[PDB]
Image (cartoon, coloured by chain):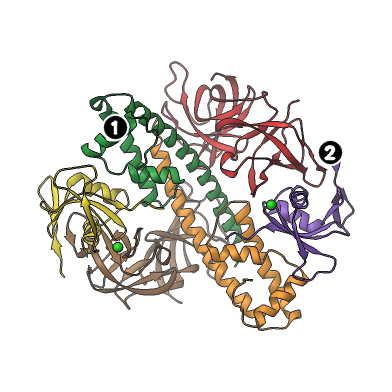
Chain colours: A red, B brown, C green, D orange, E yellow, F purple
Amino acid sequence: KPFLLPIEDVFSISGRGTVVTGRVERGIIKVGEEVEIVGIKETQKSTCTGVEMFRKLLDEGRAGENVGVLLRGIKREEIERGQVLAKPGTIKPHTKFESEVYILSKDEGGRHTPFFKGYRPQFYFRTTDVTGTIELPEGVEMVMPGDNIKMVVTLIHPIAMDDGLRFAIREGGRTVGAGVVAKVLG
Amino acid sequence: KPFLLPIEDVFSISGRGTVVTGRVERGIIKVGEEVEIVGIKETQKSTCTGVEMFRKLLDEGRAGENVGVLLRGIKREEIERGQVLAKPGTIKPHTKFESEVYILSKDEGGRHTPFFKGYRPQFYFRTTDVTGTIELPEGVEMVMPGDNIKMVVTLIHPIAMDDGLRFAIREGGRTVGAGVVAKVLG
Amino acid sequence: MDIWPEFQRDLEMYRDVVLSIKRNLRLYEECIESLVHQIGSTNFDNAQPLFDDLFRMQSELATMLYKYEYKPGKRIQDLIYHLDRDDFYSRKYWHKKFSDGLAWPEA
Amino acid sequence: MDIWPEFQRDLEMYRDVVLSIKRNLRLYEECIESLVHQIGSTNFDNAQPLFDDLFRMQSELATMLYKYEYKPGKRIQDLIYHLDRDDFYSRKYWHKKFSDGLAWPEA
Amino acid sequence: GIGKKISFDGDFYTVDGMKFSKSYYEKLWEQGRPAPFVQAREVLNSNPKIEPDPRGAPGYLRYEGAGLEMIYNPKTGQVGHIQPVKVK
Amino acid sequence: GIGKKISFDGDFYTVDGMKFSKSYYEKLWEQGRPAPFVQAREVLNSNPKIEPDPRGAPGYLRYEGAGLEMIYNPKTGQVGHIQPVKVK
Ligand SMILES: [Cl-]
Ligand SMILES: [Cl-]
């Protein structure tokens, strides 16, 4: 299974690069391997010049505890939380997808009122929130708290994703829905 | 009635001082008068070297539209939103007061659960929020959403205040109660 | 008592909002690069609605700087200064410069 | 479409949280000035629980700088550097300096 | 130094021999640059460096002082533009 | 260059001839300064400036390189303290 680390935090060290941390999602990362940084920004490539798995391993990282990865030549402003590190060519950034979503009821801590076609919530993928717009299916004018709904989402910033990727729907910091990426589009 | 302007915004201009804006609460401010800056920080004195009331007056300001006040020698970091400008000696900063409070019901958009003696909410005075602790009255162990309650409040930063000053009680940005300063203490 | 727990909450909020603002700034930057390009590829009359969008953006970025006190990267700071003045005479100047191949405002 | 309305919301949140963080920083600054004073007015043994509080604060301020990336004023930055190392040998050094009248850490 | 009324004729706000267009005046308060008459007076009283308008608007000059740059018509008293100087 | 296990004896974490106390190791990850072995190796491989520990801990030296300062015992391999250099 190809290596994937969602980025949580970033720590910059002068003249050697930047250390990014997160929990490895799948695969293995070893020192010296090339990786891509995917999502939000244009994709970039870089090499691990150091890896550490908290309490367990030096120069390799696996699923489980946190992993720090030192990327040579990557400066602080070129990387951000919400991106992923990935084996090159195994995941791509997208903005538009078909989703299956459940909208929380009010009693579940969600919305009080239904939403309409101009709803601009945040979509939370792995470690970060991204604003997106929606396209309701034909004849559906409103979605009631407590409904399931199939919708087309367009994010304002790309996110590394594949079909099956789960996400949360958020408003003001609170979870108002949960979804899965059904079909990536563009 | 002695002059009082709660500070909303601050705009610094190099070598001449800082312009502070807000809505005048009472009184009149004229160019050249001395004022105190009260609350949050240790009190300071300064002189207006310019006043403008939006669309209405130059070198004087009154209750109504926004007023900008240019304070000579006050640099940006020495003043903050939530302070007040006041005629010297007419208002003082305090941290501890007796209050009469109404706690919003859940259906009014407030809390779902009651709170206890270790409740550390935000108290909103005029233009800013300040964390404070509380002392419930004797025999009262909990306050239910929807109750009135008399409580003693201790703010972690001083606020310009007098008896009769109204405030809101806030948690995460939402209003959970409303109160009045009954008696200033210290 | 101990302020650390509420301080951490604020710090987490700070991290999240700054992350989001920087992303928004990237979109403003891209959208402006494209308007500058379009303006430089058309005649003066047809550039007016494009300038209206460009200055509207600058105005919002100026509101960010002065009302909310978010200090952006040097590039956006320079842009906020150079494009603040919006009239016939500044438009004439910027149109000329952008037509000659200027990709971002500068003196 | 138009990002300004959500951008304004974020900017208002930024203004509010920064205001609050700066206030919290003022309290850390004051509390530390007082610990430094106390430490400098007592013997080495009796200073240990005071040093424990002082370094605990520094640790939190370091978490602010490195985990959440809030960059404070120079004074607090210098403090975060100078007081990072916490052991017998750094305590011996700081106790001496604070006893001789040093009010804030510096080399 | 006492209160001087700001006059409004539908097009301009005027006081102390200075004037701002309606929309520019409102824009400055709205964008977080309040008290534009106070700002412009500071410039005029700062022994400002005075040059022709670099963009060539007729009647206008560029004034620089008190941390600000202003485009100002000494004949009409109109402040056409005012902002803080470029940050280095 | 392949995966090297970090060993733990209750008191220290050890690998590649370096070691950190249990609590210091955990503190660094917790405070947002992850991968302390990677940091210390960078210092050791940066042609660092090496001097006696200014505080005088026995066996320890101060190393400076790769943007960091470290207090390190070349005999035991223990990193006693590591942080970024002072910002000017
Ligand atoms: Cl000057
Ligand atoms: Cl070096």
At x 62%, y 71%, the residue is D106
Q: Say yes or no: labels 2 and 1 on the same chain.
A: no
Q: Is residue B93 left or right of residue E22?
A: right
| Residue B164 point in image, percent of width and height | 35, 68
Q: In the figure, B174 relative to A185: above or below?
A: below
The quarter of the image holding the N terminus of chain A is: top right
- Residue B67: x, y in percent? 26, 60
Q: Is residue B92 in sight in this rendering?
A: no
Q: Look at 20% across and 65% down and name the residue there.
A: B60
Q: Quadrant of residue C47?
A: top left
Residue in the foreground of this view, choosing between D59 and A50: A50
Q: Residue at the top extreme?
A: A138
Q: Position of residue E1 (x, y in %)?
A: 16, 70
Q: Chain of mark 2?
A: F
On the question of residue A144 being in view, the answer is yes
Which amino acid type corresponds to the residue marked 1 in the rendered image?
His
Q: Position of residue F66 (x, y in %)?
A: 69, 51
Q: Which mark, residue C95?
A: 1
For marks 2 and 1, give the CA distance.
Answer: 59 Å
Q: Which residue is mark 2?
A: F3
Residue D84, compared with residue A30, is above or below; it is below
Front-lying residue, F82 or B88: F82
For label 2, the SS is loop
From this view, report whether residue A146 is shown above or below residue D93: above
Question: What is the chain letter for disc 1?
Answer: C
Question: A129 or E6, which is in the foreground?
Answer: E6
Q: Nearer the viewer, mark 2 or mark 1?
A: 1
Amino acid tagged 2: Gly
